[PDB]
Image (cartoon, coloured by chain):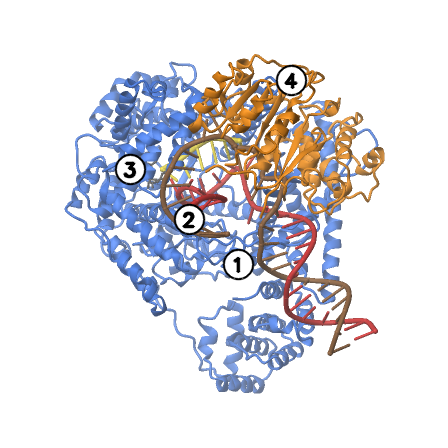
Chain colours: A orange, B blue, C brown, D yellow, E red
DNA sequence: GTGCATACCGCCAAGAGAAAAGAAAACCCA
RNA sequence: GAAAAG
DNA sequence: TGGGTTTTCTTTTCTCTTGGCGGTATGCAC
């Protein structure tokens, strides 16, 4: 399991997470503090740090350093990918609900237009990066789990192979697919550091991990785009990218009874517009122009029965 | 083997002979022959097809040319080529010199004319015209006389097929003329190929909206009919023109049926599409199967075999008729073959890629050809023609499947129109006449429709090869038992049907198994609406299943019907109609009874009472006298349940099988209130069921003394159950863990019963993992309403751990035999060959498990289908699946052997016998005789060294080729390492009261 | 004789859709 | 996503 | 030798991944 254990630029990441000096002591939900050196470097900044850890085997070190810092380090045993578990009743100490976190820390829900209340740092899984992107994206479009509590920024390491797969635009036809459009509409990626594999000593073909700082965008939800009908938009994206060489007309003749030529005339994109050459904002406004059509009643054919057959 | 394109071209030529497009097939022949690089694909059968076709026409001009093509290609003429030449010379009535010269050429060629006549598949008309051709050269040529039909002389099947002894064969209660009329009805039903039934839902009020919806649906259906006619004509002209420029098309495959029939078939499959949609490959399979079935029925109609089958069936019905007496009693198959048997033309099915592209083309034709206005909901606005069906990609993990979902306005018009009829295929409906006797793996259950002897999910499979390369007398017992099970006459219990219709038409009762209508579904906070839609869709699915079942039950309310029966690859018997049968739910078994009844006799009411106590689910551990005394104690409750099913004390609802209990309460109420209880004619089926029947067979092969006592192979005063013993061990472990304060034991308490532990204890003696037992007990804990539903996962793990701890040091011979079977299957499947074995009744059984799933992608207008080429293109056997399949499959094959022996030896005693798996049903009069015959057939089946004969057979077949010996010697160690039997006198099974109970 | 167009096939991909909440054991693969 | 039979 | 994958078997109701690009063989134009 990948764990940060080198003092190289740990103060630099600390100054990254400091932000504005006039800000109050800002909560840092560090995910998997294995060695605890990064947690110590974060505590050197002076702001409050909350540790969320999946490795309970080496648990006493974090709280033992926590009492030395007069309770700044409120260590609570939890794994970040396992908040609000999946069809599970009995809450085990590895996996627990987000309401438990936010009742223990006293911090509460804010409206979506309000300022950022919270910061998360941590790892993606070594292999399950795509799935964990999907967990965070599902929790972001459906404002549940962490993102019910506000516009939660989350800053983490990303793999090189899946980085430009998330930063892709019209262009790069080999690697431009659903997760790029799904994230980039509300994500605000800025690359903070470009560290190679050598410093990342995994605790017991170079891979260069980039810091992507996911921030939800305020202008995500509209009258047409709601946290109710986000699965319809997700199905639009994956159906459109199922046949990459096909055009928007081909996919929307199968997606809606609406004439796709008229919708593309409204959006401003031509009839020969290919899927891989269409902007991620254009997907969203395509969804919004289909959604606001009021003359017809049946606007989409997607339903949860398309989960199987 | 043959290439795919070779198979497709051969199918093209054979279809041209059927469609009379002989000029078109000759065109492809000369096109593929005049140029070189594709001519390397043409084979002998490909030329002989067009040879035989030109023979049937009596055209020398093209036949001499095709013979010249055969000589120029470098391939020698076979038997069928000279048979075609003799056919064409005999048809033209031309002089004896040419036939003399060509038959002299046949004699010079050296191959036998009797070998041209016999053991090579020709039609009887071809045989007759070759006879007419040869009778001018040799008038002294005579075919060999018909040998007498051979008699199976195996030891298990020697009491049957024996001319000595008194046999009282059963006779149906219907007379001859009524049975002939029902044969006419079923013949008309199968010629029509579809059945329309009235729905059991209450009819909607015919308002203006309903009538306008019906008119709109009618004009849309007429427009789709015309559009599909135009699309089919355009496709056939394109295929004909595409053929003319030298390419294999599908053109004869679309002229097999009439245009109206194909359009009507496509409209029928369009009508029966669920709102969620179906897979494109599924529509391809179903459309191809429907087209093939209609091709078979139409070909038998035109060829004149319908009249031959008619004239033979009127003579065959004299054996099974009450008022008609045969000179010598015999079985239905023996009487079918004793008379002049009509020739059954073995029709080779289409190859799998041909079926796939035919169904794919027909599905694409339905999608493109049908157009609808812009929205059926409020269609008054100006309309652009949007498709009726939409091709949406549905996504499950990495997998992407194409689904044809109907448009929601089409769906809304379908439930707004409230169509009062439902349409079934003729295959999916119970037969109105006694089925054709199983005389061959081809000639089978239905009158005209093709039906497989062995059900197979895969398209082309090696099962029929073993069914035809067997000795002719090997399958006689299985076919006769299939005929006997199909000959049972069924009858719908009208009172139970009335009560289930009462509950279904009103708000349903899910406690009694009647689905509630989806309109009565209940309606963080944002998740609740989606959850309600999920619940509503579950009740939408189950009520539609019940809608088919009760409609088909209402269709058969006042008519005697028959359930034809097939097998799977390992021999277990199922009724062919899938909707309404006796292998279904409690309601379906309650609706069914025997159409012929028997007087109860001196001790028949006792069997009814014991059966009723068995259906209550109470007094399961108690002896027969205790069950009879209990039935005497609840006699008033029995009469209250029978007289007042829904307006009384509702005692029958608390039973484990409520509707079956209610039907048996009605039967007991009519039997006791009769003047003479022995003279009451009873039609109710009384069931005898095996207690741990896989374990019964494991103890029978192992000859153990402890497990056999546990599974009631030793006589005892009380029944013995291992499930409750494991449940008691798990419960005392739970009490010890609740003493320590463990939370799961405190949650469980008294919830550990026989039912939650039954399937896992039943299953551990096969190659199960702990994940399978986990899901097995998780489902049983999830169906419990009183259990807290947040604790299902952790209680499932705890309960699996205590169950697998409980079975340690238990059933030693069973685990030894299962380990031997698993080891033998692993060593067989590690090599190329899959596991084969022969049942003691002689049935060959092979497993269709192979690793390779070929993509076989077929380009098309909409998408590329992905189907596994099952016709042995897959090569590497699935070792894990062979291991995990063989120990259950062998035990179920021996189950089938015991069932068939019991059926065949109860037929000679005049007993009506039907069987769910390890559940033998007979009349309440003859339960004791069935029990005695079941025990004797168990003894005779298990007095045979089944493990030892299996080992000798496996060494003889799969361990005798020289090239594998150095790799199979360890297998030779494994196969000859069967466990010893030990000491258990198995004759005591004949005194075991609770063997089947 | 040489280069270009066309058909067929292997492969590894991601929206591997989440559920990676959760168990751990044998069989196969790199 | 479910349900039924052994 | 360490990690991916599926997990007892049928039967049925309502029931198979698709697509895209490169690598190679073969026929055709010059
Ligand atoms: N889920 C299953 N998996 C494998 N085989 C099964 C399964 N259910 C039933 N069988 C087979 O059917 C027979 C058991 O049927 P049945 O339901 O009568 O169980 P049982 O063990 O005899 O219990 P009971 O005494 O309660 O009837 C055995 O031959 C067994 O192999
Ligand atoms: Mg049983």
Q: Are both tags, 4 and 1, on one chain?
A: no
Chain for numbered disc 3 = B
Chain for numbered disc 2 = B
For label 1, being within 8 Å of ligand 1 is answered: no
Distance from Cα at disc 1 to Cα at disc 3: 48 Å
Which image quarter is the C terminus of chain A in?
top right
Let me know if residue A112 appears in the view. Answer: yes
Label 3: which residue? Answer: B692
Q: Is mark 3 on a helix, strand or loop?
A: loop
Along the line of sight, which residue is nearer the eye, B744 or B945?
A: B744
Q: What element carries label 4?
A: loop
Along the line of sight, which residue is nearer the eye, A198 or B740?
A: A198
User: Residue drawn 35% across and 56% down?
Assistant: B827
N-terminal of the pair, mark 3 or mark 2, is: 2
Residue A278: give x, y in percent of width and height: 77, 39
Label 1: which residue? Answer: B305
The answer to whether marks 3 and 2 mark residues whose Cβ atoms lie closer than 8 Å is no
Residue A218: give x, y in percent of width and height: 73, 22
Q: Is mark 1 on a helix, strand or loop?
A: helix
Q: Nearer the viewer, mark 4 or mark 1?
A: 4
Q: Are both tags, 4 and 2, on one chain?
A: no
Residue A144: give x, y in percent of width and height: 61, 22
Q: Which of marks 4 and 3 is in front?
A: 4
Rendering quarter of residue B708 = top left
In the rendered structure, find residue B19 and report the number of the disc placed on it. Answer: none
The answer to whether marks 4 and 2 mark residues whose Cβ atoms lie closer than 8 Å is no
Label 2: which residue? Answer: B568
Disc count in the image?
4
Q: Nearer the viewer, mark 4 or mark 2?
A: 4
Q: Which of marks 3 and 2 is in front?
A: 3
User: Residue drawn 67% across and 65% down?
Assistant: B21
Label 4: which residue? Answer: A117
């Amino acid at each position: 399991k990948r764990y940060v254990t080198d003092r190289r630029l740990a103060e630099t990441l600390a100054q990254i997470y400091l932000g504005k000096p006039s800000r109050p002591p800002h909560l840092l939900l560090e995910c998997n503090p294995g060695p605890g050196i990064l947690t110590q470097a974060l505590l050197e900044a002076g702001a409050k740090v909350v540790a969320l850890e999946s490795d309970k085997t080496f648990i006493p070190h974090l709280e033992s350093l926590g009492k030395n810092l007069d309770g700044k380090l409120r260590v609570i045993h939890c794994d970040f990918f396992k908040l609000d578990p999946r069809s599970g009743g009995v809450i085990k100490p590895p996996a627990m609900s987000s309401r438990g976190l936010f009742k223990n820390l006293g911090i509460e829900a804010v409206p979506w237009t309000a300022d950022i209340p919270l910061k998360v740092v941590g790892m993606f899984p070594s292999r399950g990066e795509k799935r964990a992107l999907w967990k965070l994206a599902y929790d972001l479009y459906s404002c549940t789990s962490i993102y019910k509590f506000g516009r939660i920024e989350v800053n983490m390491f990303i793999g090189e192979k899946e980085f430009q797969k998330l930063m892709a635009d019209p262009g790069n036809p080999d690697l431009y697919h659903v997760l790029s459009v799904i994230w980039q509409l509300a994500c605000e990626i800025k690359v903070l550091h470009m560290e190679p594999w050598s410093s990342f000593d995994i605790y017991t073909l170079q891979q260069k991990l980039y810091l992507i700082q996911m921030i939800p965008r305020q202008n995500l939800f509209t009258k047409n785009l709601t946290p109710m009908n986000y699965n319809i938009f997700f199905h639009l994206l994956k159906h459109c990218f199922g046949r990459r060489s096909a055009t928007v007309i081909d996919h929307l003749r199968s997606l809606t009874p609406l004439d796709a030529r008229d919708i593309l005339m409204q959006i401003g994109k031509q009839e020969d517009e290919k899927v891989v050459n269409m902007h991620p904002q254009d997907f969203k406004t395509l969804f919004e122009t289909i959604e606001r059509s009021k003359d017809c009643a049946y606007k989409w054919l997607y339903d949860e029965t398309l989960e199987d057959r | 083997q043959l290439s795919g394109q070779q198979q497709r071209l051969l199918a093209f030529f054979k279809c041209c002979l059927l469609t009379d497009q002989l000029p078109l097939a000759h065109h492809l022949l000369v096109v593929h022959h005049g140029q070189r690089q594709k001519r390397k694909l043409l084979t002998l059968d490909m030329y002989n097809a067009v040879m035989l076709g030109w023979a049937r026409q009596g055209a020398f001009k093209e036949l001499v040319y095709v013979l010249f093509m055969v000589k120029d290609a470098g391939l020698t003429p076979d038997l069928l080529s000279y048979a075609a030449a003799l056919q064409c010379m005999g048809r033209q009535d031309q002089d004896a010199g040419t036939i003399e010269r060509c038959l002299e050429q046949m004699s010079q060629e050296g191959l036998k004319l009797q070998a041209l006549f016999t053991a090579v598949l020709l039609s009887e008309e071809d045989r007759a015209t070759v006879l007419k051709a040869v009778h001018k050269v040799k008038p002294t040529f005579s075919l060999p006389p018909q040998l007498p039909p051979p008699v199976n002389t195996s030891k298990l099947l020697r009491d049957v097929y024996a001319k000595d002894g008194r046999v009282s064969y059963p006779k149906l209660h219907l007379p001859l003329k009524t049975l002939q009329c029902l044969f006419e009805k079923q013949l008309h039903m199968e010629l029509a190929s579809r059945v329309c039934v009235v729905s059991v839902e209450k009819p909607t009020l015919p308002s203006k909206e309903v009538k306008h919806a019906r008119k709109t649906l009618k004009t849309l259906r007429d427009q789709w009919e015309k559009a599909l006619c135009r699309a089919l004509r355009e496709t056939k002209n394109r295929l004909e023109r595409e053929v003319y420029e030298g390419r294999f098309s599908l053109y004869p495959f679309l002229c097999l049926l009439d245009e109206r029939e194909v359009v009507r078939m496509l409209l029928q499959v369009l009508q029966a599409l669920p709102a969620q949609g179906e897979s494109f490959t599924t529509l391809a399979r179903e459309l191809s199967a429907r087209t093939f079935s209609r091709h078979v029925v139409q070909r038998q109609r035109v060829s004149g075999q319908v009249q031959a089958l008619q004239n033979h069936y009127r003579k065959y019905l004299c054996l099974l008729a009450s008022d008609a007496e045969v000179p010598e009693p015999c079985l239905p198959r023996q009487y079918w073959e004793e008379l002049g048997a009509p020739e059954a033309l073995r029709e080779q099915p289409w190859p799998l890629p041909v079926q796939m592209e035919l169904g794919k083309l027909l599905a694409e034709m339905l999608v493109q050809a049908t157009q609808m206005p812009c929205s059926l909901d409020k269609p008054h606005r100006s309309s652009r023609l949007v498709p009726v069906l939409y091709h949406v990609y549905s996504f499950r993990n990495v997998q992407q499947i194409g689904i044809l979902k109907p448009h929601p306005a089409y769906v809304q018009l379908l439930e707004k129109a409230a169509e009062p009829t439902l349409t079934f295929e003729a295959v999916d409906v119970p037969m109105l006449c006694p089925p054709l006797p199983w005389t061959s793996p081809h000639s089978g259950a239905f009158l005209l429709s093709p039906t497989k002897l062995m059900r197979t999910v895969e398209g082309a499979t090696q099962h029929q090869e073993l069914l035809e390369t067997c000795p002719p007398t090997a399958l006689h017992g299985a076919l006769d038992a299939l005929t006997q099970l199909g000959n049972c006459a069924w009858r719908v219990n009208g009172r139970v049907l009335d009560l289930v219709l009462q509950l279904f038409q009103a708000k349903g009762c899910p406690q009694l198994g009647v689905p509630a209508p989806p309109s009565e579904a209940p309606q963080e906070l944002r998740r609740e609406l989606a959850h309600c839609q999920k619940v509503a869709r579950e009740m939408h699915s189950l009520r539609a299943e019940a809608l088919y079942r009760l409609s088909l039950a209402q269709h058969l309310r006042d008519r005697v019907f028959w359930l034809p029966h097939n097998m799977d690859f390992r021999g277990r018997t199922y009724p062919c109609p899938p909707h309404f049968n006796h292998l279904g739910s409690d309601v379906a078994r309650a609706l069914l009874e025997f159409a012929q009844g028997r007087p109860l006799g001196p001790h028949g009411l006792d069997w009814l009472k014991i059966h009723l106590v068995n259906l209550t689910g109470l007094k399961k551990r108690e002896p027969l006298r205790k069950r009879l005394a209990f039935a005497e104690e609840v006699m008033d409750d029995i009469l209250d349940s029978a007289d007042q099913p829904l307006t009384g004390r509702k005692w029958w609802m608390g039973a484990e099988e409520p509707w079956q209990t209610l039907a048996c309460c009605m039967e007991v109420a009519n039997a006791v209130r009769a003047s003479d209880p022995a003279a009451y004619v009873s039609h109710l089926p009384v069931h005898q069921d095996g207690s741990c029947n896989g374990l019964q067979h494991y103890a029978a092969l192992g000859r153990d003394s402890v497990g056999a006592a546990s599974v009631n192979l030793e006589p005892s005063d009380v029944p013995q159950d291992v499930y409750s013993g494991v449940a008691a061990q798990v419960e005392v472990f739970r009490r010890q863990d609740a003493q320590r304060g463990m939370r799961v034991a405190q949650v469980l308490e008294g919830f550990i019963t026989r039912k939650v532990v039954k399937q896992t204890v039943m299953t551990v003696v096969y190659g199960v993992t702990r994940y399978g037992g986990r899901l097995q007990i998780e489902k049983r804990l999830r169906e419990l309403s009183d259990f807290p539903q947040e604790f299902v996962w952790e209680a499932s793990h705890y309960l699996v751990r205590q169950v697998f701890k409980s079975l340690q040091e238990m059933f030693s011979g069973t685990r030894a035999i299962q380990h031997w079977l698993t080891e033998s299957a692993r060593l067989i499947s590690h090599m190329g060959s899959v596991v084969e074995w022969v049942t003691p009744l002689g049935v060959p059984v092979i497993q269709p498990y192979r690793l390779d799933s070929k993509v076989k992608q077929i380009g098309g207008g909409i998408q590329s289908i992905t189907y596994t080429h099952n016709g042995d293109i897959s090569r590497k056997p699935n070792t894990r699946k062979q291991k995990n399949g063989f120990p259950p499959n062998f035990i179920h094959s021996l189950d089938s052997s015991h069932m068939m022996l019991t059926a065949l030896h109860c037929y000679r005693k005049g007993l009506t016998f039907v069987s769910v798996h390890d559940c033998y049903w007979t009349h309440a009069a003859d339960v004791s005789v069935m029990n005695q015959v079941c025990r004797e057939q168990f003894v005779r089946l298990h007095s045979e060294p089944i493990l030892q004969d299996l080992s000798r057979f496996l060494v003889k077949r799969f361990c005798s080729e020289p090239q594998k010996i150095l790799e199979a010697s360890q297998l030779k160690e494994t196969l000859q390492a069967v466990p010893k039997p030990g000491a258990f006198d198995l004759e005591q099974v004949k005194r075991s009261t609770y063997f089947f109970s």
